[PDB]
Amino acid sequence: SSFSGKYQLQSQENFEAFMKAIGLPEELIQKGKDIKGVSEIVQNGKHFKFTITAGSKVIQNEFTVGEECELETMTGEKVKTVVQLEGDNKLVTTFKNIKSVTELNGDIITNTMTLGDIVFKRISKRI
Image 1 (cartoon, one colour):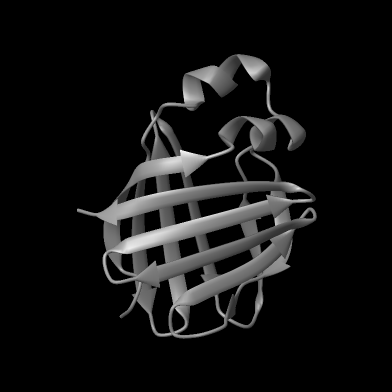
Image 2: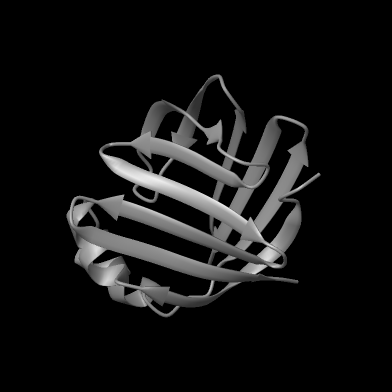
């Protein structure tokens, strides 16, 4: 279905503030800031595989929409949460006080993570 795709990053806002506050070693931060990572999605109805790639940081995630799951975050840290389908195209979850919205509009996925007052937004494009 609906999200399924290779995508790769185009633009992003506020990488830095965000990745600070989340608990990142500022070393591999500024390496990170200008990497354009690639997202593989497989959607089978309500079941998702998310494969993010930055370097040979593979993190690989899966969830079923509506049910509990365990997501590896950008830290390595693994968190129990639920991803929900508010639309047929926008995936919403909260982990560690981050609001994560993931939106497909056509061939562009937009991801907005939000930790307090910081808005970390990633625009990616289909390949």
